[PDB]
Amino acid sequence: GSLAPKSATRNPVKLNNFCQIFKKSYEITKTADATKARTGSALANDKKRR
Amino acid sequence: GSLAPKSATRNPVKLNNFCQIFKKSYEITKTADATKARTGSALANDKKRR
Image (cartoon, rainbow over all chains, first blue to last red; front, top):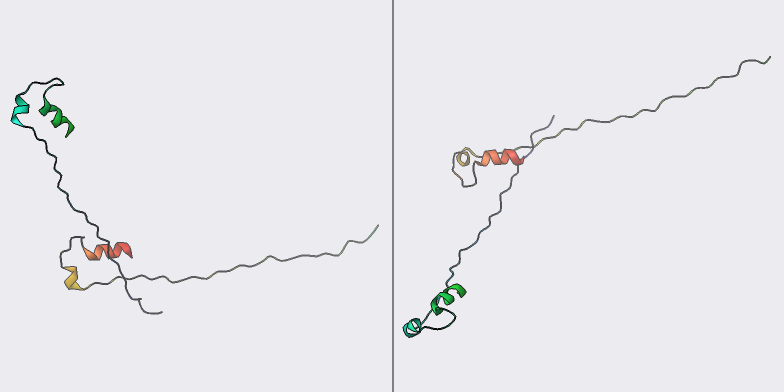
């Protein structure tokens, strides 16, 4: 024959993260582009590697 | 040609237990009840927790 008890409660936990910028670059001189060499064109191989 | 023997007996054992009273409660203001929250309605979450 007593009274009702006191109430209690809790809260969730917050989590977060960030976004990151990525960059990769390739470069070739115009003379080397026109120059014909074995192992194919240098620009395409550089693009593949990068 | 002998008489009947004297008798003997015994009794069981008794066990008992009690009853307990359990109470949990929740409470919220009517202002916070009508407010918008990203995590959802506070009353429903509190009822779930309790």
